[PDB]
Length: 84
Length: 91
Image (cartoon, rainbow over all chains, first blue to last red; front, side, top):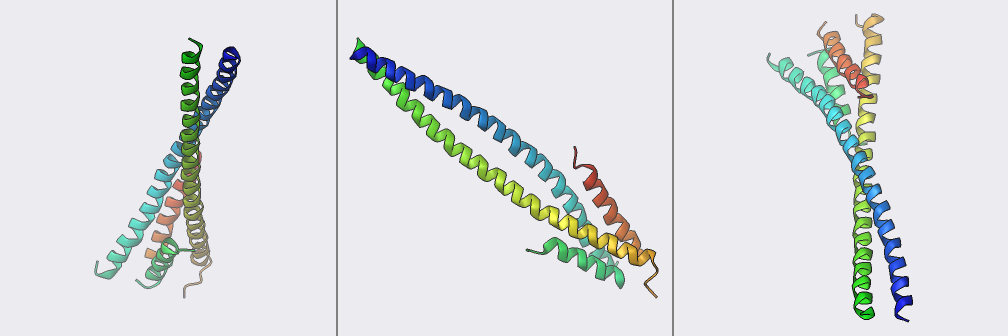
């Protein structure tokens, strides 16, 4: 009857509001994991950038103003731009 | 009466089943963003590892005199950059 249908929907509704609660919990932990990975990424990208700047600057400095130095600089450059 | 309240709670229920649907899409999006960041990481870690090997190997040839200056200066600059990257693996 009316009461039975009201009770069944109310039960499924509170069960649904539970899932929403647990899915929001997951989203907050995923937001936290993306944030950590993005903080790490900015740090490592800066170190690789410092190596890239050094490689290109030395390549320019060798040009007008390298023997074994140029050979090493080119070996580093090939490591940076390799695709795997 | 009872029909009105049944209609209002059924509407709340189907609306909440739609939010679970959209929250599951967000989770799949977030799983995809964590996966991309972890794939980048493995690739850039591999390059750092290869630069470390190269830096130490050529330092061994400069130390154990196998060249008969500016090269050692450059090798040491790279090594300091690599050490600073190792130092920030906790921070």
